[PDB]
Image: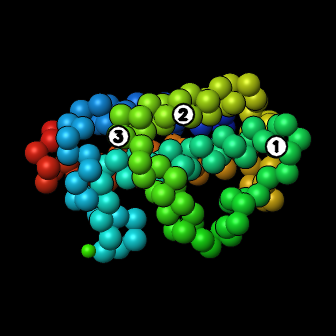
């Protein structure tokens, strides 16, 4: 649907559309301002930087790749992550923050592009039946696990960046 992809084609489209927009925004923003803690954060009342936002996106995108790739190698997978429950997603996002705290904006953007390319490759190697035809992780399809961690967060990031750019001298 327009809300949540329900086919392989829709998933690829949402990724392509939302990521193309995101990368256009990330390539526009002067890197010199990407450490200002001037964006509203995920939890209300917090603040984050553009670099921090890229770090959060990278963590979710790397995670879904790790789930799929590890499963495909016949390895057990902890969801959402080893040591975390599904009601600890803020805590998990803070792991990403620490994981990537010393990485530059430029390296983060490059890494995000790399893992986005890898998720597209994983999708391309599969079919609609694999992605949407049956459950994969408990009640959820693989395709939904992918959009939940890629196209949906990309679109949220795009909206956050549009709002922020209005107060930071950036047209986009
Ligand atoms: Ca903001
Ligand atoms: Ca505050
Ligand atoms: Cl989703
Ligand atoms: Na989906």
Q: Secondary structure at mark 3?
A: helix
Q: Secondary structure at mark 2?
A: helix
Taking the image as shown, residue 28 lies to the left or right of residue 56, namely left
Which residue occupies the foreground of this view, 160 or 131? 160
Which residue occupies the foreground of this view, 127 or 100? 100
Residue shown at the point (73%, 46%) measured from the top left:
67
Q: Is residue 137 above or below residue 10?
A: below
Q: Quadrant of residue 30?
A: top left
Residue 71, numbered label: 1
Q: Is mark 3 within 8 Å of ligand 1?
A: no
Query: Outermost residue toward the left?
Result: 169
Sooner in the amino-acid sequence: mark 1 or mark 2 = 1
3D distance between C-alphas at marks 3 and 2? 16 Å
Query: Outermost residue toward the front?
Result: 102
> Mark 3 sits on what residue?
105
Taking the image as shown, residue 67 lies to the left or right of residue 107, namely right
Q: Secondary structure at mark 1?
A: helix
Sooner in the amino-acid sequence: mark 3 or mark 2 = 3
Q: Residues within 10 Å of mark 2 (few under 14, many from 20)?
A: many
Residue 89: x and y in percent read 57, 66
Sooner in the amino-acid sequence: mark 1 or mark 3 = 1
> Mark 2 sits on what residue?
116
Residue shown at the point (14%, 49%) measured from the top left:
168
């Amino acid at each position: 649907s327009m809300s949540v992809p329900q086919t392989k084609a829709e998933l690829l489209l949402a990724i392509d559309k939302n990521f193309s927009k995101l990368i256009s925004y990330l390539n526009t923003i002067p890197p010199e301002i990407t450490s200002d803690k001037s964006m509203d954060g995920h939890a209300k009342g917090t603040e984050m930087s553009v670099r921090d936002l890229v770090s959060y996106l990278l963590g979710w995108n790397a995670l879904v790749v790790k789930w799929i790739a590890s499963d495909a190698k016949g390895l057990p997978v902890d969801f959402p992550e080893t040591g975390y429950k599904w009601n600890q997603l803020g805590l998990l996002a803070q792991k990403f923050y620490s994981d990537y705290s010393e990485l530059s904006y430029e390296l983060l953007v490059a890494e995000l592009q790399t893992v986005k390319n890898e998720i597209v490759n994983l999708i391309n190697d599969r079919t609609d039946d694999i992605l949407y035809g049956r459950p994969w992780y408990t009640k959820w399809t693989m395709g939904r696990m992918i959009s939940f961690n890629t196209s949906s967060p990309y679109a949220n990031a795009n909206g956050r960046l549009r709002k922020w750019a209005k107060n930071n001298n950036i047209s986009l």
